[PDB]
Image (cartoon, rainbow over the protein chains, first blue to last red):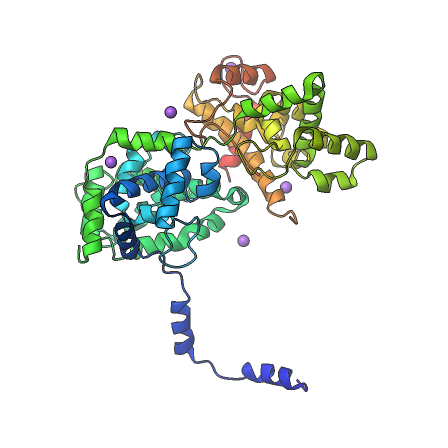
Length: 246
Length: 238
Ligand code: NA
Ligand code: NA
Ligand code: NA
Ligand code: NA
Ligand code: NA
Ligand code: NA
């Protein structure tokens, strides 16, 4: 420790820890996930009398192609690649969020979670991870669960902890399969490693207060994913069980 | 609920759907991935009477070394590096797939799936991730399954769901061992009908089922082999 710098280094480590201070640091530095209220604002500021239609179009890009704007434009129809390149220019759509408030097509989808899941269901044959992939895994996997925005519809209130956890594990059956399609590397990962890679936005979505819990519940009931008393459907229990397995 | 933006979000979800509008969007945005026609089209006119041997060679390189054309030539025989480099120049072979028109050895291999898989079986001892690997995990893992091409041959019709599922499971057992060896390489595109888009093109199901029965992976009554039933077990047992 004789050098004056190694002396300072050694000293740095000889202090007591301000636990509280380091924990505030940990909280700031910690994934919080997207802000939907400001993604909506931006879409509505930007699109005006054309924002609902532009958004629907971006959400369907989200559902079917993910965030891969450029790669996808190179393989799609000319009229599609045109709209898409335009809407990117128009809203400043990015493939990966550099900042909070960056607008990725997935985040738009998430911010409007009830629509996106209904459209996912309505367009299930166009999903890269849809009915054909989910049938390999279980029977009757609910199509509404077939997008990146489902986690924001799972309740935490008005529903038992156990329900929330079954809904999460059932959703995770899809997340697992989806993750392996988006990140081929996860095809050689353990379940837990794959689970960690989507754990953070999953919890953020479930725990967020932006989209109100009572409507998540009413919606899940309406779709049949929650029974008349707020308990997951049998298909959902079957899917959670298949996730827990093997 | 509590925020005008929240209220907007739930109100957006209460909109009745316009199926026609949303399907238009879907069809026009559908990503094609691989178009085998474009690749065979290019290889053929360009090669001429010289194309079939050039394709075979490109695919043998694809089964042994994937895309690493340059890295690969650096250490292969002079004859190997010469012929191989000649073919890159001739056909425009790239290592990464940038555009829909990009020609990689793997894409060539996947445009002719039946051949590849069959070459693969016959050159199994030269496969990077082969029997030595998979005879540890099961016995008699089908050698045809041991490559990138196979996923293109999974039948989605004319067979039972139990059969499609068994083939997907049996094959995932190889994909998974193979992806691990790549996840670790010091520094790619998998393909099958179930993950592919409405836009994509595969050998028709009946040709898939026919080839499968021919190589013995499916039996003559449509049902997967023991070696497949089994090795799908190994997968299902984690
Ligand atoms: Na690990
Ligand atoms: Na119930
Ligand atoms: Na609509
Ligand atoms: Na079409
Ligand atoms: Na290995
Ligand atoms: Na049979």
